[PDB]
Amino acid sequence: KLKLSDWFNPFKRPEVVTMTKWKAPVVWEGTYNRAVLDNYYAKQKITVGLTVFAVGRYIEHYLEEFLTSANKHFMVGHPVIFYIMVDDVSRMPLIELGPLRSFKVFKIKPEKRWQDISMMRMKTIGEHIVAHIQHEVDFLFCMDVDQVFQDKFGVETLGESVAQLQAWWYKADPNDFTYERRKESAAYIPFGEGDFYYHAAIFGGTPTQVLNITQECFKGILKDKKNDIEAQWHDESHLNKYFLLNKPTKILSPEYCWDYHIGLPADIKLVKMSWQTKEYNVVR
Ligand SMILES: O=c1ccn([C@@H]2O[C@H](COP(=O)(O)OP(=O)(O)O[C@H]3O[C@H](CO)[C@H](O)[C@H](O)[C@H]3O)[C@@H](O)[C@H]2O)c(=O)[nH]1
Ligand SMILES: OC[C@H]1O[C@@H](O[C@H]2[C@H](O)[C@@H](O)[C@H](O)O[C@@H]2CO)[C@H](O)[C@@H](O)[C@H]1O
Ligand SMILES: [Co+2]
Image (cartoon, rainbow, N blue to C red):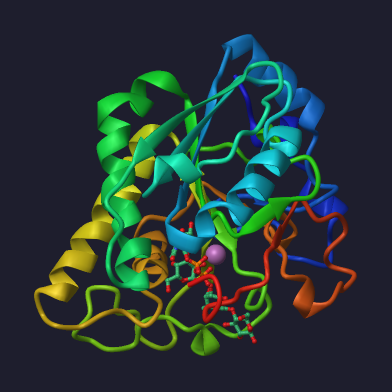
């Protein structure tokens, strides 16, 4: 079957981290052979899912740009199902989809606090995995809507459990990571521990692993709320605690989720996806 050597060459990007101590690749531009994987996964006849939430002011502008860019760049060459969660379906925009792309739309009850809106994604994703997604796709990605694909986001990102390196912290010291540091929170990580700071804007895997990711994160969210404490960065704090305990089998470089407000160092060879401008006081 498939072995890492067949498609991944860490030595092509010697100036960055390309392998972990638990044998997972960190996928950087130039390290991967997409054609080998496109052919590998086509033989298997895979379908890839993508969930996205859009609640309130986020619903219209961001969603159109997300979906337009997604149809253009996400897993082209393979069937894809876009799962869209909205609070008012009538505001869902019309986006023409390319061959082998389709979508499903679901109405969700919007939460009061912007933080619960984000954290409740974990419960909702799990419910839909059990109800249908586990039967509809072989791999699943869950993404924030306030970002845009810029180049091919393809099958090189697929794996059992996939994590995203946060662009602002990928070369930082772990003691500087913004983990949750209070021992009272289920997301607690002490200083001196941690491998990477993962971004909650992108994670994925098989429906099985995504279910465990979202279920475990949601249990921690719940246990925290029952002790009147909310983690520093909400679901992202719990996600980082999860991936510390359950190592991801694949990690995506910051090229796959870049913030141009950082600049463009030589590390970032080809951006596949970029942040939208965070406007907490305007869109939120
Ligand atoms: O009013 C809202 C609030 C949230 N969302 C959805 O929830 C996601 C998360 O909200 P942000 O994109 O504003 O969050 P940030 O990227 O700024 O901050 C980070 O921390 C958050 C928790 O504080 C989440 O974990 C988030 O995924 C992570 O990127 C959005 O992308 C969107 O999909 C909405 O649609 N509308
Ligand atoms: O720290 C988690 C948090 O990071 C935000 O990104 C900040 C970053 O924390 C800060 O060091 C840098 O100077 O500015 C970035 C842009 O605001 C993310 O926006 C947020 O989603 C979390 O991931
Ligand atoms: Co976001």
